[PDB]
Amino acid sequence: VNSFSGYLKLTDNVYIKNADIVEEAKKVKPTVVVNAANVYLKHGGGVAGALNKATNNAMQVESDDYIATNGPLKVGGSCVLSGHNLAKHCLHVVGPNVNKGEDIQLLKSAYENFNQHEVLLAPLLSAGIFGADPIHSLRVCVDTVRTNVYLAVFDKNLYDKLVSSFL
Ligand SMILES: Nc1ncnc(N2C[C@H]3CC[C@@H]2CC3)c1Cl
Image (tube, rainbow, N blue to C red; front, side):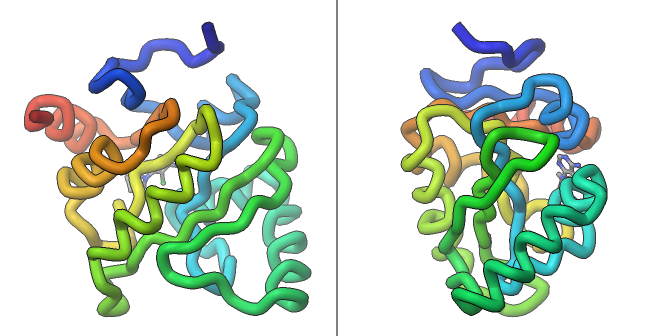
């Protein structure tokens, strides 16, 4: 049993709810919240800008030190950093950004990072300002992630479309 509430069950392991990952993280304090990161861990908008704002910029400060030591992530890659006031840990995952020309096949590699964590509060990857088709992102998620994932998708006309089109 866990603390996640109000989710629709899509499969054995994937759940979906119309909630802000920020407001959802603040309520649940999950072990892992996933950030929709870029390779530079520059949290400017969407899930990343919103998560970072909710940490009062502490996520960005920590991230800048990580990059100064380790250099940029790979597209499809991830790192584990603090969850600050939102979660125990934040898994920063880089999905491909279509608005930069990245290979959408890298989306499966991105979601494979989730399998290193038994439970994750997570966003839809490459959604939003990353430019991918969210229906495709949900299909890759279901077909790739084997651990228990709670997607918080803060957007009605899209939540309802994802549910009503889910095979
Ligand atoms: N705070 C959030 N929580 C959950 N999902 C978010 N997404 C999901 C789609 C794509 C990125 C943005 C817009 C709707 C955000 Cl910004």
